[PDB]
Image (spheres, rainbow, N blue to C red):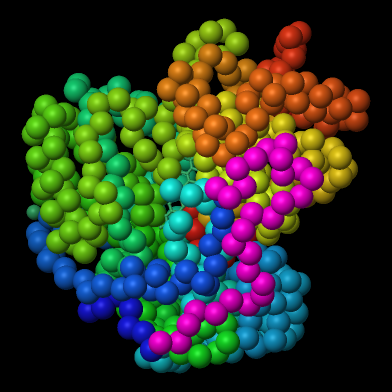
Protein backbone atom coordinates (compact mmCIF):
# COMPACT_ATOMS: atom_id res chain seq x y z
CA UNK A 1 0.00 0.00 0.00
CA UNK A 2 2.55 2.62 -1.21
CA UNK A 3 1.35 6.24 -1.39
CA UNK A 4 3.01 6.52 -4.87
CA UNK A 5 4.75 4.22 -7.39
CA UNK A 6 7.07 5.90 -9.95
CA UNK A 7 8.40 5.16 -13.46
CA UNK A 8 11.34 7.61 -13.61
CA UNK A 9 9.75 10.26 -15.85
CA UNK A 10 10.31 13.76 -14.45
CA UNK A 11 7.57 16.16 -13.35
CA UNK A 12 7.91 18.83 -16.12
CA UNK A 13 6.68 22.51 -16.07
CA UNK A 14 4.51 24.30 -18.69
CA UNK A 15 6.25 27.70 -19.00
CA UNK A 16 9.37 29.51 -17.67
CA UNK A 17 10.17 29.01 -14.01
CA UNK A 18 11.79 31.62 -11.74
CA UNK A 19 13.51 30.56 -8.48
CA UNK A 20 15.33 33.88 -7.69
CA UNK A 21 13.34 36.94 -6.41
CA UNK A 22 12.67 39.32 -9.39
CA UNK A 23 13.90 42.84 -8.59
CA UNK A 24 12.21 46.06 -9.83
CA UNK A 25 12.23 49.78 -8.62
CA UNK A 26 9.68 49.10 -5.79
CA UNK A 27 11.62 46.05 -4.43
CA UNK A 28 14.00 47.95 -2.08
CA UNK A 29 11.18 50.02 -0.48
CA UNK A 30 9.97 46.67 1.00
CA UNK A 31 12.86 44.18 1.09
CA UNK A 32 16.64 44.51 1.02
CA UNK A 33 17.83 40.91 1.75
CA UNK A 34 16.67 39.55 -1.65
CA UNK A 35 18.73 36.32 -1.43
CA UNK A 36 16.50 35.27 1.52
CA UNK A 37 13.39 35.06 -0.75
CA UNK A 38 13.02 32.19 -3.26
CA UNK A 39 10.24 30.44 -5.26
CA UNK A 40 9.90 26.65 -5.73
CA UNK A 41 10.02 24.94 -9.19
CA UNK A 42 9.87 21.46 -10.94
CA UNK A 43 13.66 21.34 -10.28
CA UNK A 44 13.06 20.31 -6.63
CA UNK A 45 10.20 17.86 -7.57
CA UNK A 46 12.42 14.76 -7.24
CA UNK A 47 13.05 15.44 -3.53
CA UNK A 48 9.31 15.93 -2.96
CA UNK A 49 8.62 12.55 -4.74
CA UNK A 50 11.03 10.80 -2.35
CA UNK A 51 9.41 12.48 0.76
CA UNK A 52 5.75 11.81 -0.24
CA UNK A 53 6.52 8.10 -1.07
CA UNK A 54 5.99 5.68 1.84
CA UNK A 55 4.03 2.51 2.72
CA UNK A 56 0.88 3.02 4.86
CA UNK A 57 -0.12 0.62 7.67
CA UNK A 58 -3.62 1.06 9.19
CA UNK A 59 -5.12 -0.40 12.40
CA UNK A 60 -8.80 0.59 12.80
CA UNK A 61 -10.31 0.04 16.29
CA UNK A 62 -13.81 0.43 17.86
CA UNK A 63 -13.38 4.20 18.68
CA UNK A 64 -12.81 4.77 14.90
CA UNK A 65 -16.04 2.94 13.84
CA UNK A 66 -17.90 4.50 16.86
CA UNK A 67 -16.98 8.05 15.70
CA UNK A 68 -17.67 7.00 12.04
CA UNK A 69 -21.17 5.68 12.94
CA UNK A 70 -21.94 9.10 14.57
CA UNK A 71 -20.61 11.09 11.55
CA UNK A 72 -22.69 8.83 9.13
CA UNK A 73 -25.80 9.48 11.35
CA UNK A 74 -25.38 13.28 10.96
CA UNK A 75 -24.48 12.90 7.20
CA UNK A 76 -27.84 11.11 6.58
CA UNK A 77 -29.71 14.38 7.54
CA UNK A 78 -27.95 16.25 4.67
CA UNK A 79 -29.79 16.82 1.33
CA UNK A 80 -27.61 17.75 -1.66
CA UNK A 81 -28.49 19.18 -5.08
CA UNK A 82 -27.01 18.14 -8.43
CA UNK A 83 -25.60 21.24 -10.12
CA UNK A 84 -26.33 21.94 -13.82
CA UNK A 85 -23.52 22.13 -16.44
CA UNK A 86 -24.12 25.95 -16.45
CA UNK A 87 -24.07 26.16 -12.60
CA UNK A 88 -20.86 24.08 -12.43
CA UNK A 89 -19.26 26.14 -15.33
CA UNK A 90 -19.89 29.42 -13.43
CA UNK A 91 -18.01 28.11 -10.33
CA UNK A 92 -14.82 27.57 -12.47
CA UNK A 93 -11.79 29.89 -11.74
CA UNK A 94 -11.01 32.18 -14.76
CA UNK A 95 -7.30 31.23 -14.80
CA UNK A 96 -7.97 27.50 -14.11
CA UNK A 97 -5.90 24.89 -16.04
CA UNK A 98 -7.03 24.44 -19.69
CA UNK A 99 -8.54 21.11 -20.84
CA UNK A 100 -6.45 18.70 -23.00
CA UNK A 101 -9.58 18.60 -25.25
CA UNK A 102 -9.22 22.13 -26.65
CA UNK A 103 -11.14 24.64 -24.47
CA UNK A 104 -10.09 26.56 -21.30
CA UNK A 105 -11.52 28.00 -18.06
CA UNK A 106 -12.96 31.10 -19.83
CA UNK A 107 -14.48 28.84 -22.64
CA UNK A 108 -16.08 26.94 -19.68
CA UNK A 109 -17.26 30.18 -17.92
CA UNK A 110 -18.79 31.42 -21.27
CA UNK A 111 -20.74 28.10 -21.57
CA UNK A 112 -19.06 27.55 -25.01
CA UNK A 113 -20.55 24.63 -27.00
CA UNK A 114 -17.13 22.87 -27.36
CA UNK A 115 -16.69 22.86 -23.53
CA UNK A 116 -20.38 22.10 -22.61
CA UNK A 117 -20.42 19.23 -25.23
CA UNK A 118 -17.22 17.81 -23.73
CA UNK A 119 -18.53 18.18 -20.10
CA UNK A 120 -21.70 16.29 -21.20
CA UNK A 121 -19.59 13.38 -22.62
CA UNK A 122 -17.42 13.11 -19.40
CA UNK A 123 -20.60 13.02 -17.23
CA UNK A 124 -22.08 10.23 -19.49
CA UNK A 125 -18.75 8.35 -19.14
CA UNK A 126 -18.85 8.69 -15.31
CA UNK A 127 -22.47 7.32 -15.31
CA UNK A 128 -21.58 4.37 -17.59
CA UNK A 129 -18.02 3.56 -16.33
CA UNK A 130 -17.02 2.96 -12.65
CA UNK A 131 -13.71 0.99 -13.16
CA UNK A 132 -11.42 2.92 -15.63
CA UNK A 133 -8.84 5.10 -13.74
CA UNK A 134 -9.18 8.78 -14.72
CA UNK A 135 -5.96 10.38 -16.02
CA UNK A 136 -4.48 13.12 -13.77
CA UNK A 137 -1.68 15.66 -14.19
CA UNK A 138 1.31 15.81 -11.80
CA UNK A 139 2.84 19.31 -11.44
CA UNK A 140 5.25 21.12 -9.13
CA UNK A 141 3.66 24.20 -7.49
CA UNK A 142 5.43 27.56 -7.81
CA UNK A 143 5.23 28.95 -4.23
CA UNK A 144 7.27 31.74 -2.58
CA UNK A 145 9.15 31.26 0.77
CA UNK A 146 11.97 32.79 2.92
CA UNK A 147 15.07 30.61 3.65
CA UNK A 148 14.95 28.38 6.84
CA UNK A 149 14.95 25.75 1.09
CA UNK A 150 11.74 23.62 0.83
CA UNK A 151 11.23 21.21 -2.18
CA UNK A 152 8.25 22.09 -4.49
CA UNK A 153 4.78 20.93 -3.34
CA UNK A 154 2.90 18.68 -5.77
CA UNK A 155 -0.49 19.34 -7.50
CA UNK A 156 -2.38 16.32 -8.92
CA UNK A 157 -5.50 17.27 -10.92
CA UNK A 158 -7.91 15.66 -13.42
CA UNK A 159 -8.90 17.36 -16.73
CA UNK A 160 -10.98 20.57 -16.56
CA UNK A 161 -13.92 18.64 -18.07
CA UNK A 162 -13.86 16.10 -15.16
CA UNK A 163 -13.54 19.05 -12.72
CA UNK A 164 -16.86 20.62 -13.93
CA UNK A 165 -18.39 17.10 -13.40
CA UNK A 166 -17.02 16.97 -9.80
CA UNK A 167 -18.76 20.37 -9.32
CA UNK A 168 -22.08 18.83 -10.61
CA UNK A 169 -21.87 15.74 -8.32
CA UNK A 170 -20.24 17.19 -5.19
CA UNK A 171 -20.27 21.03 -5.08
CA UNK A 172 -23.43 21.19 -2.86
CA UNK A 173 -22.03 18.20 -0.82
CA UNK A 174 -18.56 19.70 0.10
CA UNK A 175 -20.49 22.92 0.86
CA UNK A 176 -23.20 21.52 3.24
CA UNK A 177 -21.85 18.17 4.66
CA UNK A 178 -18.76 19.30 6.77
CA UNK A 179 -20.90 21.72 8.86
CA UNK A 180 -23.63 19.10 9.59
CA UNK A 181 -21.25 16.22 10.49
CA UNK A 182 -18.79 18.33 12.58
CA UNK A 183 -20.87 21.33 13.70
CA UNK A 184 -18.85 24.02 15.48
CA UNK A 185 -15.64 21.88 14.97
CA UNK A 186 -15.79 22.79 11.24
CA UNK A 187 -13.51 25.81 10.91
CA UNK A 188 -13.93 26.73 7.22
CA UNK A 189 -17.44 28.13 8.07
CA UNK A 190 -15.95 30.94 10.25
CA UNK A 191 -14.55 34.33 9.40
CA UNK A 192 -11.22 35.02 11.29
CA UNK A 193 -13.30 37.15 13.69
CA UNK A 194 -15.73 34.26 14.42
CA UNK A 195 -12.74 31.84 14.59
CA UNK A 196 -11.36 33.95 17.51
CA UNK A 197 -14.76 34.20 19.29
CA UNK A 198 -15.07 30.37 19.10
CA UNK A 199 -11.50 29.71 20.45
CA UNK A 200 -11.78 32.29 23.29
CA UNK A 201 -15.22 30.99 24.38
CA UNK A 202 -13.78 27.40 24.22
CA UNK A 203 -10.67 28.28 26.32
CA UNK A 204 -12.94 30.15 28.84
CA UNK A 205 -15.31 27.09 28.96
CA UNK A 206 -12.55 24.83 30.40
CA UNK A 207 -11.75 24.78 34.17
CA UNK A 208 -8.02 24.14 33.60
CA UNK A 209 -7.57 24.68 29.82
CA UNK A 210 -5.05 22.86 27.64
CA UNK A 211 -4.66 23.20 23.91
CA UNK A 212 -2.51 21.70 21.15
CA UNK A 213 -2.31 21.61 17.36
CA UNK A 214 -1.55 18.53 15.24
CA UNK A 215 0.61 18.72 12.11
CA UNK A 216 0.46 15.63 9.85
CA UNK A 217 3.71 14.88 8.02
CA UNK A 218 2.31 15.28 4.43
CA UNK A 219 -1.42 14.43 5.22
CA UNK A 220 -2.45 13.78 1.58
CA UNK A 221 0.24 11.05 1.33
CA UNK A 222 -1.10 9.36 4.51
CA UNK A 223 -4.69 9.12 3.09
CA UNK A 224 -5.30 5.43 2.15
CA UNK A 225 -7.89 3.66 -0.10
CA UNK A 226 -9.84 2.91 3.11
CA UNK A 227 -10.04 6.65 4.01
CA UNK A 228 -11.28 7.59 0.51
CA UNK A 229 -13.95 4.76 0.51
CA UNK A 230 -14.97 5.80 4.07
CA UNK A 231 -15.44 9.41 2.74
CA UNK A 232 -17.59 8.06 -0.18
CA UNK A 233 -19.75 6.06 2.27
CA UNK A 234 -20.21 9.34 4.28
CA UNK A 235 -21.22 11.28 1.08
CA UNK A 236 -23.56 8.33 0.18
CA UNK A 237 -25.52 8.88 3.44
CA UNK A 238 -26.89 12.19 1.96
CA UNK A 239 -30.26 12.48 0.19
CA UNK A 240 -28.80 12.48 -3.34
CA UNK A 241 -30.06 12.30 -6.93
CA UNK A 242 -29.44 8.76 -8.42
CA UNK A 243 -27.19 10.35 -11.09
CA UNK A 244 -25.19 12.06 -8.26
CA UNK A 245 -24.75 8.77 -6.25
CA UNK A 246 -23.49 7.01 -9.40
CA UNK A 247 -21.22 9.96 -10.26
CA UNK A 248 -19.82 9.96 -6.64
CA UNK A 249 -19.15 6.16 -6.85
CA UNK A 250 -17.35 6.52 -10.25
CA UNK A 251 -15.37 9.66 -9.19
CA UNK A 252 -14.31 7.81 -6.02
CA UNK A 253 -13.35 4.47 -7.71
CA UNK A 254 -11.77 6.02 -10.82
CA UNK A 255 -10.33 9.30 -9.57
CA UNK A 256 -10.34 9.85 -5.74
CA UNK A 257 -8.91 6.43 -4.64
CA UNK A 258 -5.94 6.78 -7.04
CA UNK A 259 -4.91 6.77 -10.68
CA UNK A 260 -2.00 7.23 -13.11
CA UNK A 261 0.16 10.38 -12.93
CA UNK A 262 0.98 12.25 -16.17
CA UNK A 263 3.49 15.14 -16.61
CA UNK A 264 2.80 18.27 -18.74
CA UNK A 265 4.86 16.66 -21.58
CA UNK A 266 2.42 13.64 -21.70
CA UNK A 267 4.57 10.88 -20.12
CA UNK A 268 3.62 8.47 -17.34
CA UNK A 269 5.37 9.51 -14.08
CA UNK A 270 3.74 6.76 -12.06
CA UNK A 271 0.65 5.81 -10.03
CA UNK A 272 -1.02 7.59 -7.04
CA UNK A 273 -2.70 5.54 -4.27
CA UNK A 274 -3.53 8.46 -1.93
CA UNK A 275 -5.29 11.89 -1.95
CA UNK A 276 -5.08 14.03 -5.15
CA UNK A 277 -4.12 17.61 -4.12
CA UNK A 278 -6.19 19.17 -6.97
CA UNK A 279 -9.67 17.52 -6.62
CA UNK A 280 -13.01 19.11 -5.47
CA UNK A 281 -13.19 16.79 -2.41
CA UNK A 282 -9.53 17.53 -1.23
CA UNK A 283 -10.59 20.06 1.44
CA UNK A 284 -13.82 18.25 2.53
CA UNK A 285 -12.27 14.75 2.40
CA UNK A 286 -9.22 15.89 4.40
CA UNK A 287 -11.48 17.64 7.03
CA UNK A 288 -13.66 14.53 7.44
CA UNK A 289 -10.68 12.10 7.59
CA UNK A 290 -8.76 14.42 10.04
CA UNK A 291 -11.80 14.89 12.35
CA UNK A 292 -12.61 11.11 12.14
CA UNK A 293 -9.03 10.13 13.15
CA UNK A 294 -8.61 12.90 15.81
CA UNK A 295 -12.03 12.38 17.52
CA UNK A 296 -11.23 8.60 17.72
CA UNK A 297 -7.64 9.44 18.96
CA UNK A 298 -9.16 11.87 21.57
CA UNK A 299 -11.18 8.90 22.97
CA UNK A 300 -8.12 6.61 22.77
CA UNK A 301 -6.20 9.26 24.88
CA UNK A 302 -9.15 9.63 27.40
CA UNK A 303 -8.93 13.42 26.79
CA UNK A 304 -11.44 15.26 29.03
CA UNK A 305 -13.81 17.62 27.12
CA UNK A 306 -12.17 17.48 23.64
CA UNK A 307 -13.23 20.58 21.65
CA UNK A 308 -11.96 20.31 18.07
CA UNK A 309 -11.43 22.86 15.26
CA UNK A 310 -10.60 21.04 11.98
CA UNK A 311 -9.68 22.75 8.69
CA UNK A 312 -8.59 20.21 6.07
CA UNK A 313 -5.36 18.84 7.52
CA UNK A 314 -5.00 21.37 10.39
CA UNK A 315 -6.33 20.29 13.80
CA UNK A 316 -6.66 22.32 17.04
CA UNK A 317 -8.01 20.58 20.18
CA UNK A 318 -8.87 22.40 23.46
CA UNK A 319 -9.60 20.18 26.51
CA UNK A 320 -9.26 19.78 30.33
CA UNK A 321 -5.63 19.72 31.57
CA UNK A 322 -4.37 17.00 34.01
CA UNK A 323 -0.97 18.63 34.71
CA UNK A 324 1.95 19.03 32.26
CA UNK A 325 3.16 15.35 32.66
CA UNK A 326 -0.21 13.57 32.24
CA UNK A 327 -0.99 15.97 29.35
CA UNK A 328 2.39 15.10 27.73
CA UNK A 329 1.50 11.41 28.30
CA UNK A 330 -2.03 11.82 26.76
CA UNK A 331 -0.55 13.52 23.63
CA UNK A 332 1.87 10.55 23.15
CA UNK A 333 -1.21 8.25 23.32
CA UNK A 334 -2.95 10.59 20.81
CA UNK A 335 0.14 10.57 18.46
CA UNK A 336 0.24 6.71 18.84
CA UNK A 337 -3.47 6.46 17.86
CA UNK A 338 -3.06 8.96 14.93
CA UNK A 339 -0.04 6.93 13.59
CA UNK A 340 -2.13 3.67 13.87
CA UNK A 341 -4.86 5.39 11.83
CA UNK A 342 -2.19 6.27 9.16
CA UNK A 343 -1.83 9.97 10.09
CA UNK A 344 1.61 10.28 11.86
CA UNK A 345 3.12 13.75 12.63
CA UNK A 346 6.05 15.85 11.40
CA UNK A 347 6.62 17.50 14.79
CA UNK A 348 4.70 15.76 17.66
CA UNK A 349 2.14 18.01 19.50
CA UNK A 350 3.09 19.98 22.64
CA UNK A 351 0.61 21.01 25.39
CA UNK A 352 -0.05 24.75 25.52
CA UNK A 353 -1.49 26.52 28.58
CA UNK A 354 -1.92 29.89 26.88
CA UNK A 355 -4.30 30.34 23.89
CA UNK A 356 -1.89 32.85 22.32
CA UNK A 357 0.74 30.02 22.10
CA UNK A 358 -1.29 27.48 19.98
CA UNK A 359 -0.32 27.63 16.22
CA UNK A 360 -3.61 27.07 14.31
CA UNK A 361 -3.40 27.23 10.41
CA UNK A 362 0.10 28.95 10.61
CA UNK A 363 -1.77 31.64 12.71
CA UNK A 364 -2.38 32.28 16.48
CA UNK A 365 -4.54 34.46 18.82
CA UNK A 366 -3.12 37.77 20.10
CA UNK A 367 -4.42 40.78 22.02
CA UNK A 368 -4.47 44.56 21.33
CA UNK A 369 -6.95 47.35 22.33
CA UNK A 370 -9.85 49.12 20.55
CA UNK A 371 -10.73 52.90 20.60
CA UNK A 372 -12.35 52.50 24.09
CA UNK A 373 -9.21 50.69 25.37
CA UNK A 374 -11.07 47.33 25.68
CA UNK A 375 -8.80 44.21 25.40
CA UNK A 376 -9.58 42.66 21.96
CA UNK A 377 -8.52 39.15 20.73
CA UNK A 378 -7.67 38.85 17.01
CA UNK A 379 -5.80 36.40 14.69
CA UNK A 380 -2.22 37.07 13.56
CA UNK A 381 0.71 35.01 12.19
CA UNK A 382 4.46 35.19 11.51
CA UNK A 383 4.78 37.89 8.79
CA UNK A 384 7.84 36.14 7.18
CA UNK A 385 5.99 34.13 4.47
CA UNK A 386 3.34 36.88 3.70
CA UNK A 387 6.14 39.51 3.42
CA UNK A 388 8.33 37.26 1.20
CA UNK A 389 5.35 36.70 -1.21
CA UNK A 390 4.50 40.44 -1.06
CA UNK A 391 8.09 41.00 -2.35
CA UNK A 392 7.37 38.60 -5.28
CA UNK A 393 4.10 40.47 -6.05
CA UNK A 394 6.01 43.83 -6.09
CA UNK A 395 7.83 42.87 -9.35
CA UNK A 396 5.59 40.07 -10.79
CA UNK A 397 1.86 39.78 -11.54
CA UNK A 398 0.54 36.49 -10.07
CA UNK A 399 -2.96 34.96 -10.66
CA UNK A 400 -3.36 34.91 -6.82
CA UNK A 401 -2.64 38.17 -5.00
CA UNK A 402 -1.41 36.89 -1.62
CA UNK A 403 -0.91 40.49 -0.35
CA UNK A 404 -4.65 41.06 -1.01
CA UNK A 405 -5.72 37.90 0.85
CA UNK A 406 -3.29 38.73 3.69
CA UNK A 407 -4.80 42.27 3.99
CA UNK A 408 -8.30 40.64 4.10
CA UNK A 409 -7.62 37.72 6.50
CA UNK A 410 -5.13 39.64 8.73
CA UNK A 411 -6.62 43.16 8.59
CA UNK A 412 -6.43 43.88 12.40
CA UNK A 413 -2.73 42.87 12.61
CA UNK A 414 0.13 45.34 13.13
CA UNK A 415 2.09 44.08 10.00
CA UNK A 416 -0.81 43.83 7.43
CA UNK A 417 -1.97 47.35 8.33
CA UNK A 418 1.43 49.05 8.57
CA UNK A 419 3.42 47.32 5.82
CA UNK A 420 1.09 45.48 3.43
CA UNK A 421 -1.77 48.05 3.17
CA UNK A 422 0.71 50.97 2.87
CA UNK A 423 3.07 49.39 0.29
CA UNK A 424 0.40 48.04 -2.03
CA UNK A 425 -1.87 51.09 -1.79
CA UNK A 426 1.03 53.36 -2.89
CA UNK A 427 1.61 50.95 -5.84
CA UNK A 428 -2.17 51.00 -6.74
CA UNK A 429 -2.19 54.84 -6.51
CA UNK A 430 1.01 55.16 -8.70
CA UNK A 431 -0.38 52.81 -11.40
CA UNK A 432 -4.03 54.03 -10.94
CA UNK A 433 -5.01 50.30 -10.78
CA UNK A 434 -7.15 51.13 -7.69
CA UNK A 435 -10.55 50.58 -9.52
CA UNK A 436 -9.17 47.41 -11.29
CA UNK A 437 -10.54 44.21 -9.60
CA UNK A 438 -7.91 41.68 -8.53
CA UNK A 439 -8.00 37.88 -8.30
CA UNK A 440 -6.99 36.50 -4.87
CA UNK A 441 -7.46 33.31 -2.77
CA UNK A 442 -9.31 32.82 0.53
CA UNK A 443 -9.67 29.34 2.23
CA UNK A 444 -8.40 27.88 -1.11
CA UNK A 445 -11.35 29.53 -3.00
CA UNK A 446 -10.71 32.08 -5.80
CA UNK A 447 -12.15 35.63 -5.39
CA UNK A 448 -12.23 38.75 -7.54
CA UNK A 449 -12.00 41.74 -5.15
CA UNK A 450 -12.19 45.46 -5.95
CA UNK A 451 -9.33 46.93 -3.77
CA UNK A 452 -11.46 50.08 -3.06
CA UNK A 453 -14.09 47.86 -1.34
CA UNK A 454 -11.50 46.75 1.27
CA UNK A 455 -12.93 48.87 4.22
CA UNK A 456 -16.41 47.32 3.55
CA UNK A 457 -14.93 43.73 3.33
CA UNK A 458 -12.74 44.23 6.46
CA UNK A 459 -15.67 45.56 8.56
CA UNK A 460 -17.71 42.48 7.48
CA UNK A 461 -14.85 40.03 8.53
CA UNK A 462 -13.44 41.73 11.74
CA UNK A 463 -15.64 44.75 12.63
CA UNK A 464 -14.81 48.49 12.88
CA UNK A 465 -12.32 47.54 15.66
CA UNK A 466 -9.78 46.36 13.00
CA UNK A 467 -9.41 50.03 11.91
CA UNK A 468 -9.00 51.18 15.57
CA UNK A 469 -6.61 48.54 17.05
CA UNK A 470 -3.55 49.72 19.04
CA UNK A 471 -1.18 48.70 21.94
CA UNK A 472 -0.17 45.30 20.47
CA UNK A 473 1.38 42.56 22.69
CA UNK A 474 5.21 42.92 23.02
CA UNK A 475 5.54 39.28 21.92
CA UNK A 476 3.76 40.18 18.66
CA UNK A 477 5.67 43.49 18.23
CA UNK A 478 8.99 41.57 18.67
CA UNK A 479 8.08 38.79 16.16
CA UNK A 480 7.31 41.51 13.53
CA UNK A 481 10.43 43.60 14.45
CA UNK A 482 12.77 40.53 14.25
CA UNK A 483 11.15 39.49 10.88
CA UNK A 484 11.68 43.07 9.51
CA UNK A 485 15.33 42.63 10.58
CA UNK A 486 15.61 39.14 8.95
CA UNK A 487 14.23 40.13 5.48
CA UNK A 488 15.60 43.72 5.57
CA UNK A 489 12.20 45.43 5.63
CA UNK A 490 12.26 49.19 6.56
CA UNK A 491 11.27 49.67 10.27
CA UNK A 492 7.63 50.37 11.35
CA UNK A 493 8.42 54.11 11.90
CA UNK A 494 9.31 54.29 8.14
CA UNK A 495 5.92 52.63 7.30
CA UNK A 496 3.96 55.08 9.57
CA UNK A 497 5.65 57.98 7.67
CA UNK A 498 4.82 56.29 4.33
CA UNK A 499 1.16 55.61 5.42
CA UNK A 500 0.62 59.36 6.12
CA UNK A 501 1.58 60.01 2.44
CA UNK A 502 -0.59 57.10 1.13
CA UNK A 503 -3.51 58.43 3.28
CA UNK A 504 -2.96 62.03 2.10
CA UNK A 505 -2.83 60.85 -1.59
CA UNK A 506 -6.01 58.73 -1.01
CA UNK A 507 -8.10 61.57 0.47
CA UNK A 508 -7.17 63.83 -2.55
CA UNK A 509 -8.60 61.15 -4.97
CA UNK A 510 -12.02 61.29 -3.22
CA UNK A 511 -14.85 58.75 -3.20
CA UNK A 512 -13.97 55.16 -2.17
CA UNK A 513 -10.23 56.14 -2.12
CA UNK A 514 -11.07 58.79 0.57
CA UNK A 515 -12.89 56.00 2.55
CA UNK A 516 -9.80 53.73 1.92
CA UNK A 517 -7.50 56.48 3.31
CA UNK A 518 -9.93 57.38 6.15
CA UNK A 519 -10.55 53.79 7.38
CA UNK A 520 -7.41 51.84 6.41
CA UNK A 521 -4.85 54.53 7.33
CA UNK A 522 -6.49 56.40 10.33
CA UNK A 523 -3.83 54.79 12.61
CA UNK A 524 -1.02 56.88 10.92
CA UNK A 525 -2.40 60.41 11.49
CA UNK A 526 -1.87 62.47 14.68
CA UNK A 527 -5.46 63.86 14.34
CA UNK A 528 -7.71 60.73 14.47
CA UNK A 529 -11.14 60.52 12.75
CA UNK A 530 -14.41 58.89 14.00
CA UNK A 531 -14.68 55.65 11.99
CA UNK A 532 -18.36 54.77 11.19
CA UNK A 533 -20.07 51.89 9.19
CA UNK A 534 -19.82 51.70 5.34
CA UNK A 535 -18.35 32.13 4.98
CA UNK A 536 -19.58 28.56 4.23
CA UNK A 537 -16.56 26.30 3.35
CA UNK A 538 -12.90 25.96 2.23
CA UNK A 539 -12.12 24.82 -1.34
CA UNK A 540 -8.30 24.21 -1.26
CA UNK A 541 -7.47 22.37 -4.52
CA UNK A 542 -11.21 22.29 -5.31
CA UNK A 543 -11.05 24.69 -8.32
CA UNK A 544 -13.83 27.11 -7.06
CA UNK A 545 -14.55 30.79 -7.95
CA UNK A 546 -17.00 33.20 -6.21
C1 LIG B 1 -2.88 35.19 1.35
O1 LIG B 1 -4.24 34.72 1.46
C2 LIG B 1 -4.74 34.18 2.60
N1 LIG B 1 -5.93 33.60 2.43
C3 LIG B 1 -6.49 32.85 3.52
O2 LIG B 1 -7.62 32.35 3.39
C4 LIG B 1 -5.68 32.74 4.74
C5 LIG B 1 -6.16 31.82 5.80
C6 LIG B 1 -6.42 32.29 7.07
C7 LIG B 1 -6.85 31.54 8.16
C8 LIG B 1 -7.23 32.30 9.47
C9 LIG B 1 -6.65 31.65 10.73
C10 LIG B 1 -6.72 33.74 9.45
C11 LIG B 1 -8.75 32.41 9.63
C12 LIG B 1 -6.97 30.19 7.95
O3 LIG B 1 -7.45 29.37 8.96
C13 LIG B 1 -8.80 28.91 8.90
C14 LIG B 1 -6.66 29.59 6.68
C15 LIG B 1 -6.65 28.18 6.48
C16 LIG B 1 -6.34 27.67 5.20
C17 LIG B 1 -6.22 26.20 4.96
C18 LIG B 1 -6.03 25.70 3.67
C19 LIG B 1 -5.96 24.34 3.42
C20 LIG B 1 -6.09 23.40 4.46
N2 LIG B 1 -6.14 22.05 4.45
S1 LIG B 1 -6.00 21.18 3.12
C21 LIG B 1 -4.28 21.18 2.78
O4 LIG B 1 -6.67 21.75 1.97
O5 LIG B 1 -6.37 19.83 3.46
C22 LIG B 1 -6.26 23.92 5.76
C23 LIG B 1 -6.34 25.28 6.00
C24 LIG B 1 -6.14 28.60 4.18
N3 LIG B 1 -6.09 29.91 4.34
C25 LIG B 1 -6.32 30.41 5.59
C26 LIG B 1 -4.48 33.40 4.82
C27 LIG B 1 -3.93 34.18 3.74
ZN1 LIG C 1 -17.73 2.03 21.49
Q: Nearer the viewer, residue 36 or 507?
A: 36
Is residue 269 at least partly visible in the picture? yes
Is 476 covered by the magenta stretch? no
Q: Quadrant of residue 342?
A: bottom left
Image quarter of the N terminus: bottom left
Highlighted range, magenta: 8-36
Image quarter of the C terminus: bottom right
Residue 372: % across, % down: 57, 7
Q: Residue at x 14, y 55 (%)?
A: 337
Residue 176: % across, % down: 45, 55
Q: Is residue 186 above or below residue 161?
A: above
Is 22 covered by the magenta stretch? yes
Q: Residue at x 22, y 30 (%)?
A: 210
Q: Nearer the viewer, residue 102 or 388?
A: 388
Q: Is residue 263 above or below residue 373?
A: below
Residue 23: % across, % down: 72, 51
Q: Residue at x 66, y 20 (%)?
A: 493
249 vs 509, left or right, is left
Is residue 533 at least partly visible in the picture? no
Q: Quadrant of residue 282?
A: bottom left
Q: Quadrant of residue 54?
A: bottom left
Of helix, strand and loop, which mostly describes the magenta segment? loop
Q: Nearer the viewer, residue 179 or 201?
A: 201
321 vs 222, left or right, is left
Residue 444: % across, % down: 53, 55
Q: Is residue 520 above or below residue 393?
A: above
Q: Residue at x 84, y 38 (%)?
A: 429
Number of on-image labels? 0
Q: Quadrant of ligand 2?
A: bottom left
Amino acid sequence: HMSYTWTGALITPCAAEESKLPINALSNSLLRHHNMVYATTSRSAGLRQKKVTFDRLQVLDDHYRDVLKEMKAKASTVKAKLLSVEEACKLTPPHSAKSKFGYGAKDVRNLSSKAVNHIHSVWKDLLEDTVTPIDTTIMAKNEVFCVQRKPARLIVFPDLGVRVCEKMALYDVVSTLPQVVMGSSYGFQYSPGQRVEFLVNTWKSKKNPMGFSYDTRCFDSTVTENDIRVEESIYQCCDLAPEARQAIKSLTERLYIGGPLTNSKGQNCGYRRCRASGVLTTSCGNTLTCYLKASAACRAAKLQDCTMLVNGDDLVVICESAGTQEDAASLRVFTEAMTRYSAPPGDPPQPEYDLELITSCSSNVSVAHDASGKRVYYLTRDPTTPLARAAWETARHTPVNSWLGNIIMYAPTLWARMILMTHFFSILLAQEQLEKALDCQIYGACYSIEPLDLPQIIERLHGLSAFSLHSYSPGEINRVASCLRKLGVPPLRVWRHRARSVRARLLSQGGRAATCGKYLFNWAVKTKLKLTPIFVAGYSGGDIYH
